[PDB]
Image 1 (cartoon, one colour):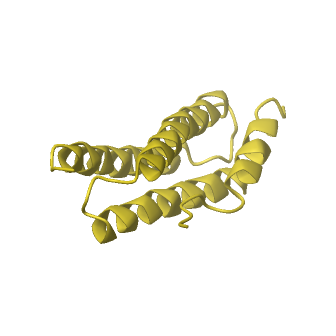
Image 2 (cartoon, chains in turn orange, cyan):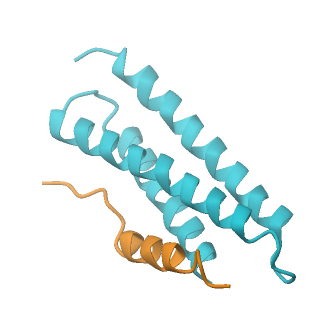
Length: 23
Length: 94
């Protein structure tokens, strides 16, 4: 067994995405 | 800052796969081959998110556009370096 995916990356992507309209 | 966080997540994701390729030279595990292809796709799309963020943020009187697009350029170069390693590696056997 072997694990390549980085923890928190989907969650950080969602924060960046949620900022997109913020004006 | 969420943008800087993604920029960091991505470099580190890219590096993780790079290190894996270095340790498992052999183009084997169909699992990880799929998984690597899945992650790399996710990264292509993450870079569109970062680019998009910059474009809509160009009016924002603080934001460092040129310093940010320079960080995205760098990440594109890193992804492209690794897509090459991966492609080269596939042509090596079995």
